[PDB]
Amino acid sequence: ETTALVCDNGSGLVKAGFAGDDAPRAVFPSIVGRPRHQGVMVGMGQKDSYVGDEAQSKRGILTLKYPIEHGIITNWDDMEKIWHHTFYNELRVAPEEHPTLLTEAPLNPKANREKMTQIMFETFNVPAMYVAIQAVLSLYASGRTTGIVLDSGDGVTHNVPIYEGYALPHAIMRLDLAGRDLTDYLMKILTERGYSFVTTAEREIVRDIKEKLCYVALDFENEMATAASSSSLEKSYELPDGQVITIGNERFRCPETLFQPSFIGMESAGIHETTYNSIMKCDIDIRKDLYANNVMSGGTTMYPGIADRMQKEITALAPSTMKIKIIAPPERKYSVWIGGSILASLSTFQQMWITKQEYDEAGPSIVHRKCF
Amino acid sequence: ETTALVCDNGSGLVKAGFAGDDAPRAVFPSIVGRPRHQGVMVGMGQKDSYVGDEAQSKRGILTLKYPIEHGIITNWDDMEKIWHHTFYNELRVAPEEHPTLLTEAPLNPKANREKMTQIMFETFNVPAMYVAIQAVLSLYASGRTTGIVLDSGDGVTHNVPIYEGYALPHAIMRLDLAGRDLTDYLMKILTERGYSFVTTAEREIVRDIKEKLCYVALDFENEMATAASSSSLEKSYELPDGQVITIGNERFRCPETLFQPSFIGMESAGIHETTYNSIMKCDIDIRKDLYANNVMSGGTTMYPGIADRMQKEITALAPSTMKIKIIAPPERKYSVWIGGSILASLSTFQQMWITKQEYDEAGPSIVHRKCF
Amino acid sequence: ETTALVCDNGSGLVKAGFAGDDAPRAVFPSIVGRPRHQGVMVGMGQKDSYVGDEAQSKRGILTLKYPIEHGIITNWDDMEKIWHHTFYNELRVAPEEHPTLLTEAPLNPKANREKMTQIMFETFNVPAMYVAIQAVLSLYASGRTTGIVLDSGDGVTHNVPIYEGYALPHAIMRLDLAGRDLTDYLMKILTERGYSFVTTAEREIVRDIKEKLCYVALDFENEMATAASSSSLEKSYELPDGQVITIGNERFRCPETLFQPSFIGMESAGIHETTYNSIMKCDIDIRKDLYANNVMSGGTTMYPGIADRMQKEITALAPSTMKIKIIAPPERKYSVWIGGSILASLSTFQQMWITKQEYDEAGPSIVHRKCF
Amino acid sequence: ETTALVCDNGSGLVKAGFAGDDAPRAVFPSIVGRPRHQGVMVGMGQKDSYVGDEAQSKRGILTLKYPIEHGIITNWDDMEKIWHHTFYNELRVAPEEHPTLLTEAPLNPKANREKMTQIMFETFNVPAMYVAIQAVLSLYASGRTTGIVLDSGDGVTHNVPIYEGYALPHAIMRLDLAGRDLTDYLMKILTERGYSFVTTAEREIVRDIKEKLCYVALDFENEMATAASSSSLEKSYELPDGQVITIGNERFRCPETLFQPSFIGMESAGIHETTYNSIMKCDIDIRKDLYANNVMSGGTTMYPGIADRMQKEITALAPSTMKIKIIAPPERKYSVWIGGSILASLSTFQQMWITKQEYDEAGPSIVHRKCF
Ligand SMILES: Nc1ncnc2c1ncn2[C@@H]1O[C@H](COP(=O)(O)OP(=O)(O)O)[C@@H](O)[C@H]1O
Ligand SMILES: Nc1ncnc2c1ncn2[C@@H]1O[C@H](COP(=O)(O)OP(=O)(O)O)[C@@H](O)[C@H]1O
Ligand SMILES: Nc1ncnc2c1ncn2[C@@H]1O[C@H](COP(=O)(O)OP(=O)(O)O)[C@@H](O)[C@H]1O
Ligand SMILES: Nc1ncnc2c1ncn2[C@@H]1O[C@H](COP(=O)(O)OP(=O)(O)O)[C@@H](O)[C@H]1O
Ligand SMILES: *CC(=O)Nc1ccc2ccc3cccc4ccc1c2c34
Ligand SMILES: *CC(=O)Nc1ccc2ccc3cccc4ccc1c2c34
Ligand SMILES: *CC(=O)Nc1ccc2ccc3cccc4ccc1c2c34
Ligand SMILES: *CC(=O)Nc1ccc2ccc3cccc4ccc1c2c34
Ligand SMILES: [Mg+2]
Ligand SMILES: [Mg+2]
Ligand SMILES: [Mg+2]
Ligand SMILES: [Mg+2]
């Protein structure tokens, strides 16, 4: 025993590695694909189902299933296959000589924590494990002890206010609008230009359109007047069949849904009011140190111009006598993992593991009373 | 002129009727809903906004706003719509030939009473009006002149000690934890079983889960051991789509928040210590007659086992040489209206109305020197 | 006309009745209470002010005023209300067909006797009246014509020597230390145990602590050593809220102030030296008959052990060749009333009344040339 | 040995330092706060409980307790923590090489002095100590030997008359209305403007509103007519969350409760009649020197206009032939400490200490026969 495993099994992308590093080694999407066609040439390298990157590169013949829906592991058979591909097939590591540090989103079902610990204690047989919380590791990568997090991953966004290491769990605002729901809205409004993107392998292409051509408008109704003079707004993208598409106001009208969720028919508020309603629900004393520390994390905070849109809109809600400081690090896509690798590298942490001999005599219901 | 109107505009339910009756005629929720969708079939009975019961049955397409937050009327445009729906559209009564008796919670802002009187004196043009206090009408329905009230409505709970018709305003203990804050905590902990109830049309469903399946545990830490042997505790409820939910220890863990407000993260005491601190702040003579008369009122005192839990916990605080007598009538959900209907039916009361010719020469500031 | 009224309006208690009986009918405290709180339920048995026992059982919401301070009637509006409650509301008697026999303490202001007679001759319109002296009716209840009285009521204590029915007015020793000044000292030293008794309804409780648990130590500095071995001295009393209080050397240190008035900061001598200096201001031949007749009266002589303490301390002052005989009846709390009912029942007395036709032609200044 | 410690452990603020100085060094509130939230990041500077200023600055996550209620130490575990924070963590001094001079209010329980001496003689092990009286050091800072003090701290107010170094302890008038009871009334009447200040960390904000915007009205009913023309009376205050609040006639209605305690429902009189009743209970030959020397002390006498209101209201009680002279020094907030630092600097005082070898052979009951 020298080091520990840090697995940030997100809903859209698995980020794993070793503790003590700075960048994760195994970064691959959490996709399981079964082939949906006949396969006349039986043999010669054909498997029952593909996982990770090899299900991404063979995706014309596959139907691609994500096992994690909204931070919630729905298909426990495919999730066990992703962890099997994570340990053996990309870290080349034995599970039995490394403690693991899983994460999860807050406000998940309790059955999600119980089954992750049970799989790690007879399917892989880790020595000890620990299920952290994704948003408090985002501060702890940032070198802070106080701030509100906007951890906008692929399945869920969730605010967590921390003041000096103390979580305020009544002010956690979990929302169910993230990079899956922006992708599935971007497919819906690429139809009006003509492009029918229907399959589950075509949502892997619209996800790549979104990661290249989408930005956040600083003023939305002003940019909707710029598309009337449709000149410099349009850019192009070459599909995997060599076709080019043209995309106009759909570049910014897709990440506007983070700030006006009524485009996809949600009765909730944007991420500017969900952050502001997670500060008003805190105590009146700590609102200086929460307005001055807004930490973004996860991949959906990587649109160009989103740290300038939140600061333009929280300022319109917070009173004008104090500064709003959106803090977006450049590596904020991997920031949950980096804080996990820092956490498992501490010396004040090794009493906080959940060892197997402490597990089995106390049952898998132990993991809830060890977190929050 | 024969009779008077009695309107208990609560924060969660409007209860109105005529003076001298025994049960209110119009009992409808104080909800204003605007439609959040498009409405392609323009015409054929479509209005801009729905109030009351018709905003409850059509709530799938509406965003529902309660205009009374914590006993404080915030949206004066929509509170005017509920009174308009109260008089014309459910009592079928003209306002101009009936003096009305509004109520309110104690320790409200003074701007709340000034606007309720101003709206009644040019929007509806009532002859006279009177704004009572909700907790002293709860004794006066009970046929008492002495007692401490626990009027636990939908927005605010407040102790009001009355000794022999003399109010002790330095001992009124207003608290901000009631049936909204129990609903919003029950939505938070149904999530740990899996059920994401997010919209404002879904807090109308969790409010009905609370009114059917939640009880108060007599011993909370004993009932948490019963949920370990999870046998006779779980009951099922059928959603309006047809799904079933299996609520477990969330049945009693929701009304525990009345007795331990730190679950929703409040720095205030439970309703057993708020009652006992509202008696210690009284004079040492009258504590015989306040321990012997604990009157519950309002809707949030209707959980099965709350009159047995308050008596079990005030006894742990009060000295053991005297009896604690929680007095809970079966009609205590309507007990504020009944005492108001008795009060407007008295003969020693018709000089206490605030007539319009007395209003307009003195102004809207007259209403404060006519109460307490 | 058959019988006469006898009203011993003390400073702390009104004792009234008819002449010729042996016990007074109306024994109620001379308290007038106005309600200090608000009064939300206007009616149903609410009055501007309460007197006597109904101001005692409702005293949690009242500010209680004694209108007789140190034997001197200071509030003539409230004293008129105690007499009105005395005649109509507790004797059920008309004033106009009964001559009344008021009393008073000696050495009072002359304006006190004038106003008592002026009120009785137009407010109540009694036929005739007579203002006696309280201490000379204490011998006359005891069946003596020679003695020295220690009439220790609630406002004033005063020695009155009488030899053979001849009062010696130059040896009357009025002192201003009585049951109010012991109550207000007992409140001051119940604070050192922790108990804060502040209001004028809490002095109605400390007065009842004094009437149950206070005694007179035979040797004071010997009993202060018993409080060092704090074993059998302490007793417990139960408040009306149910809190038991512990009380040790405050039991006897409260009636020590009668014997050492420097505890409440008086430049006067105790009741043993006031009695002895009231005897050595008399003639040398009658001192054998005043030492052998020490009649006690008033309520503050009812502490257990005060006849044993006065006899132990006058003997330390009187010469050893002559005996001291403290005479304390069991009904000496009522002894001023009993002697007044004997006096009004005599046949050698009916020319001593002050009739109204003798009043009005001679003025209000007649009552002074009829007593002493 | 060169110098001595002077600790004025008040109810709302600890004022300590060394003898012989002119201003105290360690001024910090006597607050012990425990964290009430979860604490995810265990380590990195987290403690079980915070004291003093660090419990004030981190107060959003704390529940703040004052250990001294009404001059009475009600939590001996936390009071021991404030003395420990005083000696080591803000004076940086050893207890064992400095005699200390504690103070207390008059008329405290006897158990309060015994436990303060017991803690100083085994927990900190001082050489010698001395418990003074807070009001008699307020004269002795002022350079007087004759005067009456109105020492109005944070827990209690109390008058102490002194004529030429002789305390008149039967005229000491302790009251239980001070800067806590004015803060808790100011929270009650800030609610009628709309502001709910509920938590014990929000009473630390209302205490800072009181120290800025409150003044004593010279004529109360005249200023209540000024609030009808609500023009020059309102001022604004910026909360820690940057919300400005507007405050009108609550600026003077809060310190009016010092002069009319029936606003918070007390059966006591204001500080002008308590001072006047403390002078009339003294001897008639010294009332000229007490009317001419009214010394104020403690922080609650620092409202603008309180020396002009006492002089306006004692003059309406005292007879017109003798002058009233309210003497308020500008450093009267620290005046109890300054007179204590003078007292421990005298040469006629070193026989008045209570040394440990005098303590242990005589017991903890020695401290009471060494004062007054
Ligand atoms: N450069 C980018 N710009 C915009 N969105 C991105 C970018 N990169 C990734 N995303 C979105 O963020 C998601 C990945 O975020 P991540 O933090 O991995 O979420 P999770 O960890 O929950 O899987 C992807 O599904 C994608 O939709
Ligand atoms: N039978 C019940 N059991 C439990 N809770 C109830 C019941 N009836 C109503 N409630 C709760 O109490 C609230 C109604 O209280 P109510 O008396 O209407 O308050 P108000 O009239 O002051 O608004 C509802 O919001 C609901 O959450
Ligand atoms: N049994 C008792 N023991 C001790 N003190 C008593 C007792 N009864 C009455 N007192 C005190 O004496 C007072 C009553 O004396 P009382 O004869 O009524 O005087 P007066 O009639 O002149 O007012 C009461 O105020 C009470 O303090
Ligand atoms: N400048 C000020 N104006 C008005 N009130 C003040 C001011 N400063 C302090 N106070 C009040 O006085 C109290 C402090 O008085 P202090 O002398 O510290 O009392 P103690 O020392 O007995 O605790 C505080 O609680 C505060 O409410
Ligand atoms: C369940 C949980 O929230 N664990 C958790 C998350 C994050 C975090 C960051 C930094 C820490 C430092 C020291 C100790 C711990 C312990 C748990 C923990 C953390 C830390
Ligand atoms: C402002 C207010 O509290 N009014 C009020 C409340 C309740 C109540 C009950 C019974 C009453 C009987 C007679 C008169 C009044 C007057 C006001 C009033 C009441 C009553
Ligand atoms: C003023 C006065 O002291 N009158 C008084 C008191 C007591 C007393 C007792 C017995 C008496 C017998 C006969 C006559 C009188 C007259 C006055 C009188 C008394 C008597
Ligand atoms: C218990 C007590 O009141 N001690 C006390 C207070 C104040 C004071 C002032 C000045 C003094 C001068 C000389 C001696 C003493 C002794 C005690 C004392 C004082 C003084
Ligand atoms: Mg993630
Ligand atoms: Mg109600
Ligand atoms: Mg008497
Ligand atoms: Mg002080």
Image: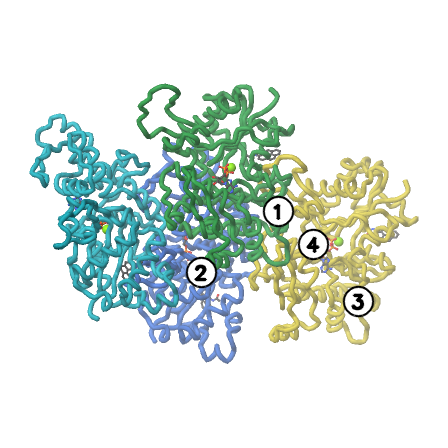
Chain colours: A cyan, B green, C yellow, D blue
Residue behind mark 3: C326
Residues marked 1 and 3, same chain:
no
In the image: residue B212, left or right of residue B185: right
Q: How far apart are the alpha carbons under marks 1 and 4?
A: 39 Å
The residue wearing badge 2 is D67
Q: Which residue is mark 4?
A: C155
- Under circle 4, the secondary element is loop
Which of D241 and A202 lies nearest the eye of the viewer? A202
Of all chains, the one bearing label 3 is: C
Q: Which mark is residue C95?
A: none
The amino acid beneath tag 4 is Gly
- Give yes or no for contact between labels 1 and 4 (Cβ–Cβ under 8 Å): no
Mark 1, other Cα within 10 Å: few <14 / some 14–19 / many ≥20: many
For discs 2 and 1, the disc positioned in front in the rendered view:
1
Q: Residue at x 59, y 43 (%)?
A: B162
Residue tagged 1: B293
